[PDB]
Amino acid sequence: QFGRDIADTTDAVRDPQTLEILDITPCSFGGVSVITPGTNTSNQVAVL
Amino acid sequence: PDPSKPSKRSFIEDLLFNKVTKF
Ligand SMILES: *[C@@H]1O[C@H](CO)[C@@H](O)[C@H](O)[C@H]1NC(C)=O
Ligand SMILES: *[C@@H]1O[C@H](CO)[C@@H](O)[C@H](O)[C@H]1NC(C)=O
Image 1 (cartoon, rainbow over the protein chains, first blue to last red):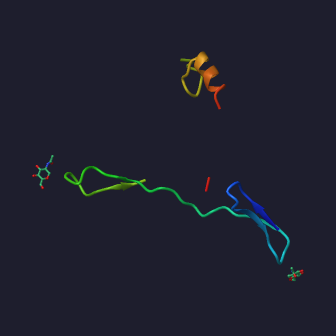
Image 2: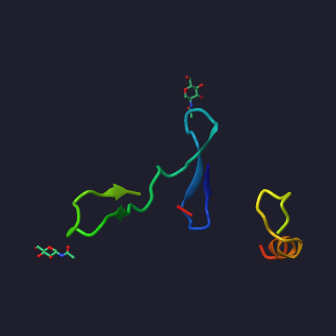
Image 3: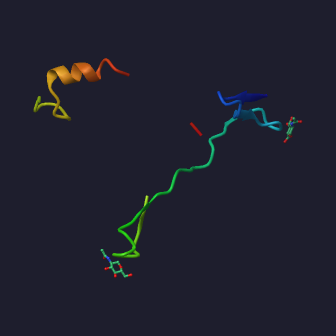
């Protein structure tokens, strides 16, 4: 009924009403970095 | 360096790169 990944998290599931398999891919994420000249020069920043 | 490659590496360097290999 359920599949699992190395972390024991759910990898895929079988839909309980219609028996098809759905992959579960966690929603996009990532670190956010701010690129900035010192604030003694400018308050403009770029975001990575 | 070998000018014919997509990355100008030498013959020997290519050999080295071909030997060393969530949510
Ligand atoms: C869910 O409903 C459908 C009809 O739309 C039926 O064919 C199916 O067997 C039902 N699933 C379960 C698990 O009862
Ligand atoms: C930084 O800003 C101060 C004003 O608060 C100014 O006196 C100082 O000379 C500035 N230094 C540089 C390196 O821009």
